[PDB]
Image: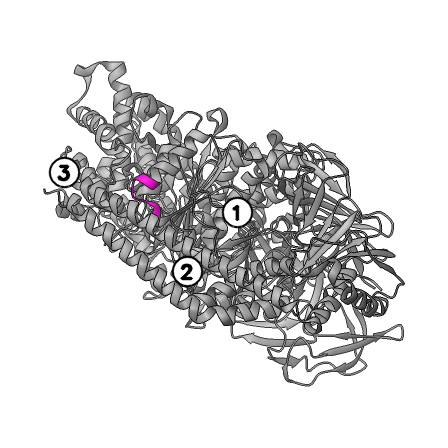
Amino acid sequence: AAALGSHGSCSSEVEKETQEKMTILQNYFEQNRDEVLDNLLAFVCDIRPEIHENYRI
Amino acid sequence: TFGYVHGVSGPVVTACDMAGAAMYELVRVGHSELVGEIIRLEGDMATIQVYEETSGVSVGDPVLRTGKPLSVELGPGIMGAIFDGIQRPLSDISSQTQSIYIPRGVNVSALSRDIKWEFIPSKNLRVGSHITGGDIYGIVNENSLIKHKIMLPPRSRGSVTYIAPPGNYDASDVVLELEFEGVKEKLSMVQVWPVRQVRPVTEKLPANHPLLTGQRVLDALFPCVQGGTTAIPGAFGCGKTVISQSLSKYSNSDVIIYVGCGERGNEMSEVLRDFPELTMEVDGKVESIMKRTALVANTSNMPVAAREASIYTGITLSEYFRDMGYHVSMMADSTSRWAEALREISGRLAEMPADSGYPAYLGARLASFYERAGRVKCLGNPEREGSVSIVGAVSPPGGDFSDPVTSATLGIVQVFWGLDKKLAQRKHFPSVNWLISYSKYMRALDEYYDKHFTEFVPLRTKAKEILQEEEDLAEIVQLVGKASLAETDKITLEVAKLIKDDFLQQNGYTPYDRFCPFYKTVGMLSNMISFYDMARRAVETTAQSDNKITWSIIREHMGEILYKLSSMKFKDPVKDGEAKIKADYAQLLEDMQNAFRSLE
Amino acid sequence: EKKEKQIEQQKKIQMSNLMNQARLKVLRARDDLITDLLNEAKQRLSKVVKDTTRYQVLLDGLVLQGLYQLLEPRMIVRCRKQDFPLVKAAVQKAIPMYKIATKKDVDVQIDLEAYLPEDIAGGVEIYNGDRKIKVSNTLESRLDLIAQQMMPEVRGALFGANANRKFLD
Amino acid sequence: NYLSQPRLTYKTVSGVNGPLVILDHVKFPRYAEIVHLTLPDGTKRSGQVLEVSGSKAVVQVFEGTSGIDAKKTSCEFTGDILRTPVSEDMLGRVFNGSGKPIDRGPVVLAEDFLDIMGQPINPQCRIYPEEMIQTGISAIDGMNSIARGQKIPIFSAAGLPHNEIAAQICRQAGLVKKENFAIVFAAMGVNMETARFFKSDFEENGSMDNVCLFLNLANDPTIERIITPRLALTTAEFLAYQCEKHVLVILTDMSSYAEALREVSAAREEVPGRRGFPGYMYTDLATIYERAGRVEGRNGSITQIPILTMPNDDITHPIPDLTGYITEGQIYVDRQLHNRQIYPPINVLPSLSRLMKSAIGEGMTRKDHADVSNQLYACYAIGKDVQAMKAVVGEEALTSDDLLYLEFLQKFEKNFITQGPYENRTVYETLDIGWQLLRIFPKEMLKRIPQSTLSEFYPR
């Protein structure tokens, strides 16, 4: 019964900690997504054309 | 100049524009500079066995030819270095990369540049002097114990055009320039040698002096000569470390090399951790053995070529130190794991299996390796002798000597120190089985012993006979009990037990047995055998008498001599002078003679 | 007596049944957020291609880059129909740079008969003359390729560096 | 930085031969390059380049070549070798042989990419193994104790319960507790029942937050079975040597892996070596097994326990033989014990942990432990000798001393070795069971133990 009586408390706690972690993710996401996207988009949009370096001539 | 990759299949890389290559020429492959050896030419195409994993090599990648076959850089900075089997410095590949791995595509120079050393040019030389391979044109003081003698490479010769003055120099400095046939050769303290080629000598000599290990059983009953070839059955249950540590931390050998053929990863790190902590006494100072060695360590996962090269790098380093006039000694931790690297490279080469799986050449590779040992007159002019002693461990499956590497090794080596798990389970350290073990160098040490220890050959002969007689008598003891044996047999068994327990056995952790000098060893055995002959005299002299002497009467009236004989091991070469030890042993001879006279 | 020890593991089991799923929902959230950052990036690329100035600079790159991989005597560029004038300019600027870098002549065509699907967020495909070898240089392809390789930098910047990374080795 | 250049795709399938597809007119191919084949019907398949030569690239396709053709087939090249996306979030999760997850969770957000082939750990940097891992099975922890950083295979045979032992180690394993430990369990050639057993038993019996589970099924394509060990070890190297975690890697059947090296070597047309295995099988198993040990300046540590089905029960077979050469021990599962319904049926006589004396002792476990294990081995050995004597001489001919060794033997198999699938005995509970048996003897019969240790632990 000491283990069994802990289950509902643990069930609520894992949801609380999931909601907190997902909130932390959403906060980090909203704080960082702009800079991250701008970096990726800039690398997409900066082509830097190169030949393969093994080309002899 | 350089070629280009044409194809790859597993570790085998085909290249093109290789027209100027040679078979077994060393090559760098790929943008990451992977190491490999050419194993076929096909015209302007060549096939390279790559060592490291070829994953990510591309067609059209560069293939730089190295101007040399597989080779060892030789010079200052060897001492205390740890190399792998293809001569890459594992201590520096650590400290320079700050990584726990060997990165695929290492290019670190084997003897580290920019490190200056104190170089003394040989003050006897002048510009215009004649010079030849093996001439000591200078010395590098790289460590207090080992003056590194520089020498002209064996292929080089000519007249000195310039020599550096005394000072601090490194591998990039042109220490020497010489001319021959109108052509100048520039030279450095670093020298290079093909690893599979013997370094030549003025004359290979007959070996005639003991490689004193400070270990009674070895040094007395199975002496290995300096320059001798020997094997140890290296297996976990028998304590192979005992011999290899004792050889390094005491034995009469100026420089040690140790080759990890292909050891288990942890057991290799055990050695590399532990050896730096060993110390030996020199000039009344205590110093780390890393002043007198270099370790060529390969774990089982190092490339197949690095395992099969391991012993050839080791011997090449050892021959370079031999040509400085040192009595080098080289361990190989498992010639069996080197023989597996042979099986694997022959498997990749698709060569036919000979004995049990091994290549046809396994016996010839072993034999042409072991022949690199011996005492020699060096090349060049200062006339010095040197040697390489080879201590090649073997690991026969279940102890079965019919195993091809073990069988060929016992065919070639002149000494076998047969360690035994039974003796180790009984804690009979050094645990060498004296019945199985042998040395073919007995004859060759007659000259030495006749000069320095003229009684010792009689003593050794008697000792082996006494122990052999006890092994035969033990069958009678099992059949009919100790009570049934003759008095001569009973005293022989008691003395053989004394020899076994208080002479063969030696506790190398104790201050008195951590090492054991040869004079100590002789004096201990001399007393035990002098006691045997006088005890046996009293027994046999009282054959057919009314009162007959027996071992029990000897133990009753003079068991103090038996107690003293067992006690003779405690004498200490540090706290007791050599003369004091000899005097105590001479006193025990007088004591026992007077005690025997009280009976007969 | 053994069961009275085992109930501590039953507590750990019930904890694991809950925890192991709860953290999978956090991981699912992480990957959804990355997937939405890629969705926003694809939307932003679909905005960028509406500027003919920057889009010309993109095509000038993407075309020349395709050619520099597929070194051949004859090549075909495939593009969306409406982009063709910008692509033609890109090909005409790329051919000189092809000769300069490759040291060999080329014939390049745009396949006006076989335009790419209109819903692609711009960029080009390039095929060799045999139509047996191709390279795909759509902005969506580069976004997938670069986002996949930069994923550790994405994670580390987006959700912060993990303090357990004591060594980078 | 990264491959900023776009991926080529070819229709140039010049041939197909068993599991191989031969592209031609290929531009600068890499050996071991990953490719994505697309069938005529649009089905994606992975493959890797198994050979290259001039214009040709021989891809081994992962799945069989069923449905490939010389025309409508197309083949994208990634430009790169196989890198695993790796992270600490690979704990608590279940992966197929390719490293695609199958626990219904999302794809891995890599904390870094790593080369799956790894690199050799520098022998200067490897550090000696010197503190015990508790596996909880008494026949391991009290007789064959594992130093963290040891490699020690469980040899077994077809039909024996080595998969239940492997699962029991994976649930029970951890630090001694005089938090920062995680198993990586990798399984190859697993029949789908045994794969359900691992996935289900690990998810059920509390383990998952400290384990990574790689499954390669028996019918997963054979190159994925070669990939899985390297994949798992690449994760273990990340967890240990970058994230400071202690790790135990469990490899479930190295024989099913040797059975894969056969196929890939035949795919290269290499001539078969000793007993039909590749000649380089020693090096390949070393490049699996030696991805292990502690290292200089990291708290992290990889142990390995390779489970290994000896074909035909033969220790001379190359798979156990080579493994015995590379790894610092062996643990033998025995059909004699399994038929007696003893579980776990580890035979403690031929088993040996070569690092035991550095795993265990004072501070690391308990002071007595190194003494007790020698004595238990001696009593079990003399017990077996006496049991053979009883069968010859009959009970009344036994001495009082023999009857003690026989009573110890009986109680030792029925209490020390026998443990059941969920009884997680600590080292301390194993030693207390060791004393509960050794106390059957008169104090003076326990001749391997020091008189001090007896005076400190023989009293109850």
Amino acid on which disc 1 is placed = Arg
Mark 3 lies on residue: D443
Q: How far apart are marks 2 and 1 (CA)?
A: 18 Å
Q: Which of D359 and B434 is in front in this view?
A: D359
Q: Where is residue B70 in the image (x, y as percent from the top left)?
A: 71, 57
Q: Position of residue D67 (x, y in %)?
A: 68, 33
Residue at left 70%, top 35%?
D68
Amino acid on which disc 2 is placed = Cys
Residue interval drawn in magenta: D203-208
Amino acid on which disc 3 is placed = Lys
Q: Distance between the residues labelled 2 and 3?
A: 48 Å
Q: Nearer the viewer, residue B17 or C157?
A: C157
Of pointers 2 and 3, the one earlier in the residue sequence: 2
Q: Which of B119 and B596 is in front in this view?
A: B119
Q: How crowded is mark 1: few (under 14 residues within 10 Å), some or many (20 or more)?
A: many
From the viewer's perspective, tell me whether residue D190 is left or right of residue B572.
Answer: right
Q: How crowded is mark 2: few (under 14 residues within 10 Å), some or many (20 or more)?
A: many
From the viewer's perspective, tell me whether residue D242 is left or right of residue B74.
Answer: left
Chain identifier of the residue bearing label 1 in the image: D
Question: Is disc 2 in the same subunit as disc 3?
Answer: yes
Mark 2 lies on residue: D243
* Callout 2 secondary element: loop
